[PDB]
Length: 272
Length: 272
Ligand SMILES: OC[C@H]1O[C@@](CO)(O[C@H]2O[C@H](CO)[C@@H](O)[C@H](O)[C@H]2O)[C@@H](O)[C@@H]1O
Ligand SMILES: OC[C@H]1O[C@@](CO)(O[C@H]2O[C@H](CO)[C@@H](O)[C@H](O)[C@H]2O)[C@@H](O)[C@@H]1O
Image (cartoon, rainbow over all chains, first blue to last red; front, top):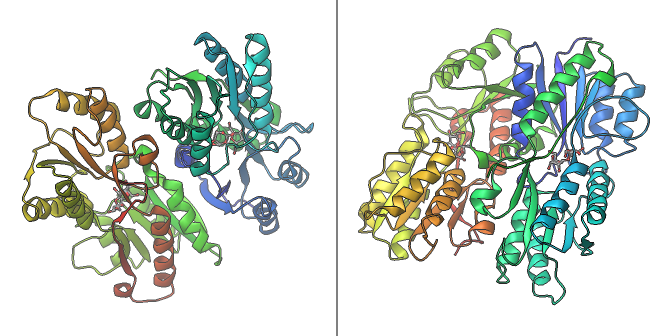
């Protein structure tokens, strides 16, 4: 029956600059006007992704679940739909299931990122994307590919690293990249964490941000510009996301239809 | 109850890496039947609110708190009411309770030493609000250090580590535009440091030549951006682990005098 618990299920493997607690606080700020408690339930990696979900349903430990790192064909989404556990996703699946969700428009972000580099005079653009299994990788990759076409620029190919690749190695990669004779003039990053490491490596090779190369990056809080005011920054509002995920879940638990409980936040360029 | 309540002020720093603390806790709780509820509160005027509410409701078997004052009402209240708890920080009021803390005194002392070693003569420090015990630890270590290393303090009282970053930056710029400048800085916050450096740089000041900076950080981040910052690591994930172990043992009867630890300043490998 009523547990008055919202389970937040988070992978322990997150980024340096995930500002995860801002997400936690957005959820909890909404839940404070209610009788709901927020339980944080970690899982370590991919091999145990379904473990906490099965465990919530087996013990009946939560009235609703928040999940993230959504795949287009997500077994968690399907399992909780079938088992009638109210849930909301941070991200979007694409499997013909209408569920509550909130996501950032990574497609629009990568498209507008290419445009901006093109406006900066840039002609050869690389992008650093998530692992391909997550839906937001396909959103980003799509927005970027569409952008390289619409803005009459070309892609500098990049397969080496990803958004989840070790920072020390992003840094080394960035250093060797700007010591190559073949190098790009623009970078789209889908992680503020990857961007930090990338810039460190760039500077280590005599490269000046804004001069020799332009960078567009997302960030989940306002940090990159104290650090490097020349980075073209886009804010992803992680606290807002936490608020919206909570809003949606509460309404789903009370029987509002999932179709009305869906939002997508748009990229906003940092005032910084 | 099977619930550990993590009581957290929503007012945290940008670079708090709070989730790293959360994950240290859950990593330990995973071998147990305990669930971690995250319980926020907004400010100081409601600090005791979640504490009274946990005990009125009986909604937890143990509590984790932080932002510890030397004469902390929460600590006294929970001691009196026999609610197992552990503090991230230390009180100083004749009550022996489980705790884990970081040695802020030793950090500020070793900070001043390092700056002295770099040939610096006039050292400023940015400390927390006076009400919290770690402020007194830091201010003490700094005070001893200025004496022991034959240098002088540059007086500062305009800001704290809880003062807004934009205002820290503006303060850092005007500070270097003055004819009275410190040549060394001790920071008790990775967040303030970031804003601080941005302000210095906007005044044409170079980190490592014109001024040296020692800063704590709760994860390895300061050196990617600014390699010349003398970084000390506070291990927040270890903190989370220790808080959890201590609380578990305290819940099962262990004497509090035996559940106390302080981690020491560790100089970051990415530091000069
Ligand atoms: O858990 C991933 C989840 O979030 C989104 C939103 O863009 O992808 C993000 O992953 C992290 C979640 O906070 C952040 O670093 C940033 O929001 C973004 O990379 C979803 O698309 C995805 O399901
Ligand atoms: O939460 C306050 C609590 O932590 C200590 C540990 O040094 O002070 C810290 O406050 C935050 C804890 O994560 C961080 O900003 C930073 O690690 C430090 O300033 C305790 O002394 C205090 O009670």
